Image: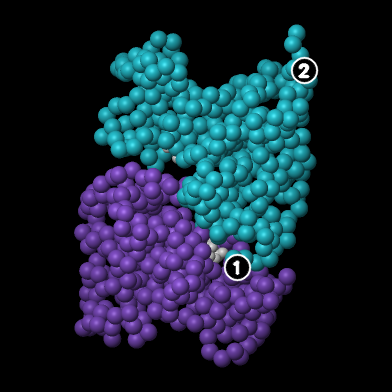
Chain colours: A purple, B cyan
């Protein structure tokens, strides 16, 4: 089979390029402005994903600059990057077999819901990844099931796709047309330009709700439809809430408990209500979300995956990761963990 | 079977309540905030559609107020309206069997595309409905295949769903979150608040392109994706063009030759029409009346034009003074010689 050899620069560390050979290339994904392939590294045999995007040589690639700064167990790792050819930038990433999207779809069209233990594991790891990037001022801006990679057997989740990510800086305006439909925060729908990283939290909340319901909680082909669905659940925004973020129906909130199926864990519902809040500043921070009681089972000395394996890394927090509220380490790192 | 009798107010004319009895009610449509039923009138056995929406006791219904002013052969007719019960407003409309959406989906999954003669008829009638509402300053704001009703046998198209419509007043700001995904004008994606009725033209262009392609021309789950698809076709917006849409870090891509965008043997005139509809600069897009006069529709003006099934085409030239008001002279092109024959 065709063997390709390039001189690629390690994602992290010093700019010291090395020769890398790979083979067995096959498209495994796309995107409006991208193509992803899977390939096997010739020496290690490890599988990698290679994201190829047209790059304007005259400028710096933001996705690349952001990924080079990230080192977290819940964020897909950038192994190397290299150019090829119009010039293309190629991001060689760790290969991850699944997405929360594909997995959720399996349960949905099987008429079942993902067991709660997995909802806990996946959401907890997503919030860890968010606490980490937010600590650098980086907002992902495209949190959705398709960007959440999963390894089925280890239950490890890895946030991926930083093509919409950006460091948010007070006073600077940001485009409001980022983020996928169903997962957009209300302020985004209203065209806000001074939004914060809390838009990622709203999205995380939509993912949680969706994993619990078996379908998107705020569907809709237009912004107006999405606003209506949001309003049918949260109730009409008070004027003050709208300001924080109007020809809309005056509707009373729908009992969060009646939104979900009966049997849905109370803690899960409570978490949702603290994520999907109109007022951006009232939503939990990702670190606070990790500490929520819904995740207490993950901190149980005896929890194990359904396949019998131990849970993946969950407590290896760093100072960087806890910076938004250090005292939470008392909750986040159980007595038995190290 | 159950018979429902209600007292309803006429759509237009004197407010003289009518008593209406209908049966065989069944759901035929939905909306995040609505439900449409089909019903059979007891007297004539005619079918009608009834759009039921919750009504703010505290406001007047804009969709209703707008529909009461419309009288056009390419706009679904509001027959009566009445309240029922929380209070609901019920709009009784003429029943139309199909949508451009369903028709297009059938051809698309059958690996076909509808005869261009239908593309001409549907688009022409859509542009007539737009020239008419725009002449009143009314912008639909939700032009998409599902809101284009069709009668398969007569080939008559009727614009429906004025739940997003609004009279655009210069100097006034408007929400940018209206309009379905694939059909949103770029200025809407950029969050413009001072957009005009030309956003309906962009949408009409997306419908045309989609009818020609067999699928949406600018798909995408996020605004960014849509902008990329738009850019892959139109090319990167110039500095000035960005200022026209109003309210940018996208790769510089050159325009894709429109001809290369559509299947082989797509009519040149169709492609040309698209290019004049899907323009970045809002003011550069054709007006709907100008669109009706485009050469792509010349065949509809031919005296011997017939529907494939052999019938005559629907009325196409009964233009009113209101319809032509945006540019009266165009009538020299819009009303063909044979249609001016007194006989
Ligand atoms: N490291 C990886 N391992 C395995 N599959 C991957 C990896 N990275 C991307 N993919 C897959 O390819 C798809 C598209 O990759 P992605 O990075 O998100 O491209 P994109 O163009 O930025 N996408 P988007 O803007 O979300 O439409 C993902 O949803 C995954 O299913
Ligand atoms: N006069 C009619 N005759 C037959 N079917 C109709 C009629 N009006 C509406 N429908 C159907 O019902 C669907 C929904 O009606 P619609 O008026 O658009 O509700 P809506 O809540 O405003 N929809 P939307 O905002 O587009 O999601 C339409 O797309 C048609 O398929
Ligand atoms: Mg993605
Ligand atoms: Mg992306
Ligand atoms: Mg509709
Ligand atoms: Mg509507």
Where is mark 1, residue-wise? B249
Q: Is residue B343 left or right of residue A191?
A: right
- Depth check: B298 or B58 in front? B58
Between residue A262 and residue A274, name the one nearer to us.
Answer: A274
Chain containing mark 2: B
Dots 2 and 1: beta carbons under 8 Å? no
Q: Position of residue B206 (x, y in %)?
A: 62, 44
The image position of residue A40, as x and y in percent, is: 58, 75
Q: Mark 1 or mark 2, which is nearer the start of the sequence?
A: 1
- Label 1 marks a residue whose chain is B
> Compared with residue B207, is residue A242 higher up or lower down, i.e. above or below?
below
| Residue carrying label 2 | B338
Q: Quadrant of residue A114?
A: bottom left
Residue B135: in sight, yes or no?
yes
- In-front residue for pair B32/B342: B342
Inter-mark Cα distance, 2 to 1: 54 Å
Tell whether B188 sits left or right of A310.
Answer: right
Residue at the spot 35% in from the left edge and 61% down from the top edge = A244
Viewed as shown, does residue B186 lie left or right of B39?
right
Callout 2: CB less than 8 Å from ligand 2: no
Task: State the image quarter where residue B238 is shown.
Answer: bottom right
* Image quadrant occupied by the C terminus of chain B: top right
Kind of element beneath mark 2: helix
């Amino acid at each position: 089979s065709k063997v390709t050899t390039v001189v690629a620069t390690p994602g992290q560390g010093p700019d010291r390029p090395q020769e890398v050979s790979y083979t067995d290339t096959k498209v495994i994904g796309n995107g409006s402005f991208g193509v992803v392939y899977q390939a096997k590294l010739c020496d290690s045999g490890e599988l990698v994903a290679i994201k190829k995007v047209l790059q304007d040589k005259r400028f710096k690639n933001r996705e690349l600059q952001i990924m080079r700064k990230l080192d977290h167990c819940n964020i897909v790792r950038l192994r190397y990057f290299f150019y090829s050819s119009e010039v293309y930038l190629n991001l060689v990433l760790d290969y991850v077999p699944e997405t929360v999207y594909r997995v959720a779809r399996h349960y949905s069209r099987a008429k079942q819901t993902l067991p709660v233990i997995y909802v806990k594991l996946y959401m907890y790891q997503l919030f860890r990844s968010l606490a980490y990037i937010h600590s650098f001022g980086i907002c992902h801006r495209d949190i959705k099931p398709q960007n959440l990679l999963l390894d089925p057997d280890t239950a490890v989740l890895k946030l991926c796709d930083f093509g919409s990510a950006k460091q948010l800086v007070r006073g600077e305006p940001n485009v409001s047309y980022i983020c996928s439909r169903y997962y957009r925060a209300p302020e985004l729908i209203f065209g806000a330009t001074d939004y914060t990283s809390s838009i990622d939290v709203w999205s995380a909340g939509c993912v949680l709700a969706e994993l619990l319901l078996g379908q998107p909680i705020f569907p809709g082909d237009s912004g107006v439809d999405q606003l209506v669905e949001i309003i049918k659940v949260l109730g009409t925004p008070t004027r003050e809430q709208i300001r924080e973020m109007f020809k809309f129906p005056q509707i009373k909130a729908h009992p969060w408990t009646k939104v979900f199926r009966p049997r849905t864990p109370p803690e899960a519902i409570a978490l949702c209500s603290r994520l999907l809040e109109y007022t951006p500043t009232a939503r939990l921070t990702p670190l606070e979300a990790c500490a929520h009681s819904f995740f207490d089972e993950l901190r149980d000395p005896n929890v194990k995956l359904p396949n019998g394996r131990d849970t993946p890394a969950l407590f290896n927090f760093t100072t960087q990761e806890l910076s938004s509220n250090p005292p939470l380490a008392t909750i986040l790192i159980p007595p038995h963990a190290r």
